[PDB]
Length: 106
Image (cartoon, rainbow, N blue to C red; front, top):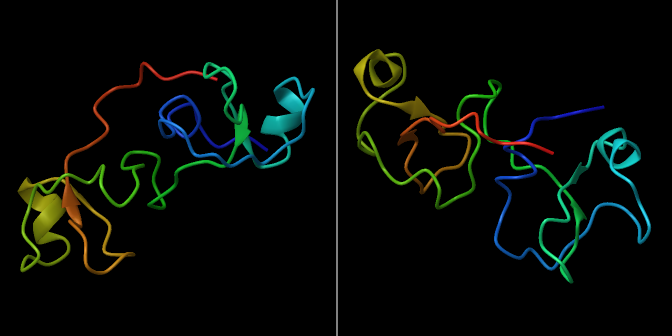
């Protein structure tokens, strides 16, 4: 397995949750469909990803979607000349800015 780097590196500042085991390495953590950072000492190094779209372009939790477009806009038209459009989760900004990074890692 292997999701992405933004799904690990750009995870969350303290999730108090893990998706691996104490003493892991990484690959084995990235092969279990889980992510691994460790960057944060003490907290859970091995955790889960942060998917939010069928395309590794959005990626973001209910809060990282800022709020590009409007909750009144629709699909197609959104991505038309707006930003990401993940309505998968109602009650949030579907039209949000793109990760616009790529400086993520494992």
